[PDB]
Image (cartoon, rainbow, N blue to C red):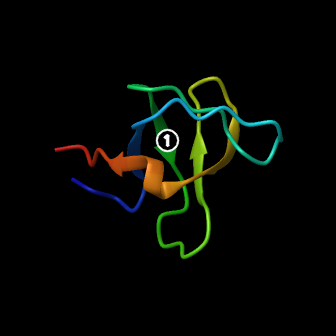
Amino acid sequence: GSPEETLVIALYDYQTNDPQELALRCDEEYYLLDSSEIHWWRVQDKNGHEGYAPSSYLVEKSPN
């Protein structure tokens, strides 16, 4: 139970001002797309919104 794609949780409320970054909410989670990364982790909201998200300000939820 861990197909490349997974979910993440934003530790802190990180608000952005660009369509490249995705607005994050504390306690909220998102759909992880690019995890192999080295640069910026892509995330997608259940609302169809996507953007970059600091991997440092979140943690892998990993479904059991």
User: What residue is at 49 percent from the left and 36 percent from the top?
Assistant: 30
- Residue that extends furthest to the left in the rendered view of this protein: 64
Horizontal arrangement in the rendering, residue 53 relative to residue 36 (left or right): right
Secondary structure found at label 1: strand
- Residue that extends furthest to the bottom in the rendered view of this protein: 38
Crowding at label 1, few (<14), some or many (≥20) Cα neighbours within 10 Å? Answer: some
Q: Determine which quarter of the picture holds residue 21.
A: top right
Q: Quadrant of the C terminus?
A: top left
What amino acid is labelled 1 in the image? Tyr
Residue 20 image position (x, y, % from top left): 79, 48
- Residue that extends furthest to the right in the rendered view of this protein: 18
Q: Determine which quarter of the picture holds residue 50.
A: top right
Residue 5 image position (x, y, % from top left): 43, 55
Of residues 16 and 2, the one drawn nearer to the viewer in this rendering:
16
Residue 11's place in the image compared with 52, above or below, is: above
Horizontal arrangement in the rendering, residue 21 relative to residue 45 (left or right): right
Give the residue at mark 1: 31
Q: Determine which quarter of the picture holds residue 27.
A: top left
User: What residue is at 41 percent from the left and 46 percent from the top?
Assistant: 58
Residue 32 image position (x, y, % from top left): 49, 49
Residue 1's place in the image compared with 30, above or below, is: below
Residue 56 image position (x, y, % from top left): 45, 56
Of residues 45 and 18, the one drawn nearer to the viewer in this rendering:
18
Horizontal arrangement in the rendering, residue 22 relative to residue 5 (left or right): right
User: What residue is at 56 percent from the left and 26 percent from the top?
Assistant: 46
Of residues 16 and 29, the one drawn nearer to the viewer in this rendering:
16
